[PDB]
Amino acid sequence: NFNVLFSTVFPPTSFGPLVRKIFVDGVPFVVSTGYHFRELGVVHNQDVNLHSSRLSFKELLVYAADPAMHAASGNLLLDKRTTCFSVAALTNNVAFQTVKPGNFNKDFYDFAVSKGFFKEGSSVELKHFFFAQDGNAAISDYDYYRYNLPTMCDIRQLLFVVEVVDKYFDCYDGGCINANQVIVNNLDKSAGFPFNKWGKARLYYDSMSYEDQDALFAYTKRNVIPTITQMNLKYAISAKNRARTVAGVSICSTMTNRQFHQKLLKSIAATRGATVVIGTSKFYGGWHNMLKTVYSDVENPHLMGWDYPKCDRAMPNMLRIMASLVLARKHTTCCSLSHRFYRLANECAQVLSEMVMCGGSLYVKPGGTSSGDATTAYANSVFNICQAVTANVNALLSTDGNKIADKYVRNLQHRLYECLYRNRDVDTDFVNEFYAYLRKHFSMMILSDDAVVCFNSTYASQGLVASIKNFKSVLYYQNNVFMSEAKCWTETDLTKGPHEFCSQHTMLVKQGDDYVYLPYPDPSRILGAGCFVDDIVKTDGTLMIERFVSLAIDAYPLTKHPNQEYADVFHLYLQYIRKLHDELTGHMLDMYSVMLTNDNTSRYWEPEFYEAMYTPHTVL
Amino acid sequence: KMSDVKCTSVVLLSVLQQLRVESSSKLWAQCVQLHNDILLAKDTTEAFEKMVSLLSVLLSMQGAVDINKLCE
Amino acid sequence: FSSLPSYAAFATAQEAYEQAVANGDSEVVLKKLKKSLNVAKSEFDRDAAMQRKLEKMADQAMTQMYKQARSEDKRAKVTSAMQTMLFTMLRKLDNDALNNIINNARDGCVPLNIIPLTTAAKLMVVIPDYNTYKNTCDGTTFTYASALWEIQQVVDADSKIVQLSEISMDNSPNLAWPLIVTALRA
Amino acid sequence: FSSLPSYAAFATAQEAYEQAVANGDSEVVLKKLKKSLNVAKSEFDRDAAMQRKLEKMADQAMTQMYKQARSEDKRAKVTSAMQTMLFTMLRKLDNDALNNIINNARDGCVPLNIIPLTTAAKLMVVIPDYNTYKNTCDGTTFTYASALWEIQQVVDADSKIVQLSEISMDNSPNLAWPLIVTALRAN
RNA sequence: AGCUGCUCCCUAGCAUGCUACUACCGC
RNA sequence: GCGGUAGUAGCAUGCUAGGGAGCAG
Ligand SMILES: [Zn+2]
C-alpha cells in the first residue's frame, strides 16, 4: 500500500525485468534475473547461474517465454495511437486485423415470416447481430486501459475486510497437487506466445514427463518468470458494437497455476448451498434451489442486483493482490513462506504487469486483471465480496450514533471502529460476530462479478446495512468508476425473482402441484442465434439439427409466459425441427432408395423431451 | 420491413468482404461504419438511404456481372 | 429378418414342438426338443442380432459421409450463392431508390464513388452513350438515386471539358463518350 | 483359432462320435460320445477364447507404445526448433552498445525498457493523423529519446510507399491514415 | 487463437450388475 | 429335484476415454 504511492514518482522506464547478460556454451545470452514491481519493490532470482554448459528442456522453455531477449532484439517503437507505454516492435510492419460479419441463414427466416413473425409493431424483434470492425479494432480496445489509475487503499479498513472475506471462504480446502493429478479438459487450445508457432497445448503437455512439470513448478517457488501475453478478438453475437478482447496466456503460466490452485478451484465448483454459486446448474430444478437459498431467513427482504462497468480494466492492483492472497491463504502446510511469496510474485509478474503483445509489437499492461488466465472467475468473486463488505462497513460506521435505537448495533458500531482503527491484530471473536450479523441481514449470491443481494429492508432504510448508493460511493472512491443507476436494479416483490441474473429473467410458474422459478432468456437472443451464424455449414439445417435441439431446450420456459408472442418462438422451433428431420429423411431417400430403418426421433419434436430438463430428478 | 433491410445489409457486407474490398483501408472503414449504422437504426428511412449509399460501393466495382445476376 | 438360414431350422423345430404339444405323448421325447429347440434360438438370435446392428452401422456411416460430402460441396460455392441470395432479396425489397440505381448500373450509369447523402458533397456518374443521357440528365438537373442533383462539370474520356449545350444527337458521335458528369445534391 | 492342439482333439472326438453314431451300437456309446463332446468342449472353450483375449491385450499394448514413440519424437523436433529460434534471434542483438550499457551498471542488471531505448538501430512511428504528424516527424530528421533520427520509407495502412511531399494539409484526407514512419539512428 | 462452469447428441472400452439359454460337477 | 462353476446372447446402470454443438461470466 505504500509502494503503490511512492512509485508514481520515479520514471516508468526503469520498471519490469532486471535482465543481465549471462554466458552459456561460451555465448552471451540476455535473461531476466529478477523483477521490479510498482507495489512489491525489487525481487531477485535465487537459482540464476552464469556459465551453463547445455540447456535442458525446462531451460529452453523458460528461455523461450521471457520477453527479455525478445524485446532486446527488436526495433524501437513509438506509438501515438495509445497512451500505454509501448516497448518494442519485433516485426517490421504492423498488422491490422479486422472482424468479419456473421453469415445469414435465410431458410429459417423464411420459415419465421411464414408463420407470422417479425410483423411491424411486434414485441419480438431482432436486436443481437454480428457486428463488424475496421482495421485498428484491437488497439482501439486495448487503449481502454487508460481507465486504470494508481490507487491508494485505506489499509486500516482493508485489514478487516480481508478477514471477513477470508471467513467467507473457510468451508473449502486446497493445496498443491502433483503432476499426476491435474485435469485438463479440451487439450487442443493455443499455447500463447511464442509457443503457438509450433503446436497446441497437447504437444507441450506431452513432451514434458511427469517430473519435468514438477521440477518446473518447484523451480518457480524461488524464481520469477516474466511472460508475454497475446490479445485476441472474440467472434460472437452481441447487442452493442464494442469489440471484445481476451488474453491468451503462455503455457508456462497455466502449467504451474493449475498445479497450485486446482484443489481449491475444484473444491469450490463442487459445493452446493454456499455463497459463491459457480458450478451449480439451473437445470433439473437447480435454479429454484439457488433462489430459495438466498431468501434464506431475512426478515423484510428487498432484492438488489448489479454488474460492474468494464470490470477487468477498471480494477485496481491492490484488490487483485488481495484476491490472490485470499486464494493462497490455505497453503499453511504444503508451502513454507518464501515459496508462497515467490509464487505471488510470479502471479503478479504474469497477469498484472506483463508485456502484452497487441498486434505485432510488445506493449506494457498497466494493471487490471487479464481475463484469460487460470483464476479470473474466482478472483472476480473475491473482489466482489470485498466490495460488498466495504460497503457494509462504510454504511455502518458513517451513521449518527445517537439516533440508533437498537442497543445491540450501537455496540457493533463501537467495537467495529475500535477493532478497525484502534487495534492492530485480529479479533476473531468480533470477526465471527460481524460475519454472523452480515449473513443474517445480507444474504448474497455470487458469480464472476454478477451478484444478487437479498437484504433486510427496515435496516437499509436506516443505514444499518448497505444500500445501492453505498456501492456507488465505494466504486467511486476505490474502483474509480461511476455506477450509473441504469445498470443496477432493485426489486421489492420476491414473488418475482431477480429482474436479471446471468442475463436470464425469473418466472414463478406452476410445475406439477407446486410453484417453481424458471430462467427464461431474451427471445431476441434466441431468434438471433437462429438466424445469424458463422461458416457455411450452418446455413443448412440438415447438417446440424442438434443446435436447434439445444436452442429449443434453452427457449422452453417461454412456453409458460403470459405474453403470447413468446411461446410462439418455442412452437416455431419445434415445427422447424420437425421439418428439418422429415426433409432430411426425404433427401436421403431420394439419393439412396431406403430410409432410416429406425430412429426414435419423434421425442425431439414433442414437448415431453424438453419438459424433463426442468423437473427435479436428474437422469445424467 | 426494416428486418429485410438489416438482413440484406448483412448479406451485402458479406459479399463485399469476400470481394476483396478490405484491401483498401478507407473503403473498408466506410463500409463497416455504414453496416453498423444500419444494424443500429431504429427507423426505416435513414436505413434505406444508408442502404443505397452502401450498395453504391458494390455497384461502382466491375467484379459482379450485373446483367447476368438479374436474370429475373 | 426372416430370410436367414437358421430361421428354417427354427421353424422346423417349432413345428415339431407344436405337433408334440398337440399330441402330448411323452415327457422326454418332447424334452429332446427343448435340447434341440431351445438351442434353435441360440444360432438364430445370435446370427439375427449382429446383422441387425450391422444394418444401422451402415446407415449411420452412410449418413455421416453424405453430410461430409454436402459440407464439402457447400463451402466451395459461397461466392455465387451469396450474390444470388442478395439479388433475390433486393428484388423482394421493392424500393424505388434502389431499383433506379440498379437499372442504371445494368445499362451503364455506375458511380465512381460512394453516393453522398448530405445536401452538399460531390458525385460522379459515368455515362457511356447518349440514349442513357436522355433519361437521366435534362437541362441542368440530374436525376439519380431518386434525387435531384445539379450538373456542373461534364467531361469526355480524353480529359477535355465538354460544354453542356454541345450535347445533342447529331454531334454526339464527336465526343469520347464515357462522360464523367460530376454533380451535387439538392 | 484353427491350428491349436485342441482342434485336432475336438476333431478326433467328433469323428469318433459320428462314426459310432452311424454305427449306432449302444446307448452307452451315445453317452460316451456326448460326455466326450461335453469335455472336449472345455478344450475349445479356453484354448480358443482366452487366447482370443491375449491378442486384444497385445494389440492394445503395441498401439500404446507406438503412440508413445510418436510422443517422444515430437519432443525432439520442438526442442530443435526452439533452440534454433533462440540461436538465430540472438545474432541480431549483440551490438557493442549493449556491452557499453551493461558494463557501466553497478551490478550488471539493467532494466529491460531501456535496452531498446539506447541501443535500437531503427525506430518505428505510428501516426493517426496529420496533426500528430506535424509535431512528431516533420521534415527528414527528428529527435526522439534524446537521439537523432533520419526518415526513410514512409508507408500507410495498405503498405504502399508514400513520398514526403504528399503529406500536406489538403492532401491528407486522401491517405490511408495509420501512417507508419520508420527512421534510422543518425550519428 | 483465452480461462472456467453447466447441458444435449454419437461411438468405443472396461468393470459392475441384472435376466434368459447351453454344458460340467457332486449333492 | 437343488446348488455351484464354466459358456453364449440380451438388457440396465455407472465410470472413463474420443468426437460434434449450444448457453452463461
Ligand atoms: Zn503449496
Image (cartoon, coloured by chain):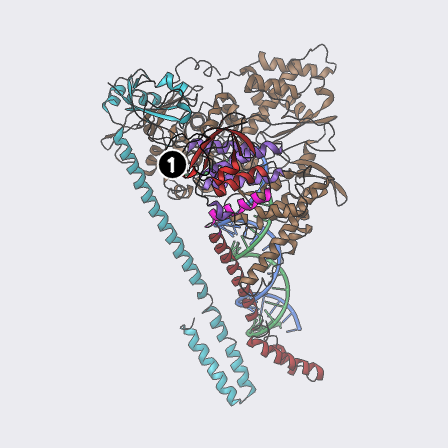
Chain colours: A brown, B purple, C red, D cyan, E green, F blue
Q: Is residue A430 visible?
A: no
* Closer to the camera in the image, A200 or A392: A200
The answer to which image quadrant residue C14 occupies is: bottom right
Above-or-below relation of C116 to A577: above
Q: Total number of numbered labels?
A: 1
To which quarter of the image does residue A391 belong?
A: top right
Per the rendered image, the range of residues in magenta is: C74-95
- Magenta segment includes A228: no
Determine which residue is flagged by label 1: A215
Chain containing mark 1: A
Amino acid tagged 1: Ala
At a point 56% along the width and 27% down the height, the residue shown is A382
- Give the percent coordinates (x, y) of residue D77: 32, 44
Residue D27 located left or right of residue A291: left
How far from the left and from the top, in percent, is residue A176? 47, 35
Q: Foreground residue, C133 or C112?
A: C133
Mark 1 residue CB less than 8 A from any atom of ligand 1? no
Q: Nearer the viewer, residue A250 or A336?
A: A250
Mark 1 Cα shell of 10 Å, populated few (<14), some (14-19), many (≥20): few
| Percent of width and height locating residue A158 | 55, 18
Horizontal relation, residue D159 to residue A402: left or right:
left
State the residue lying farthest toward the front. C170
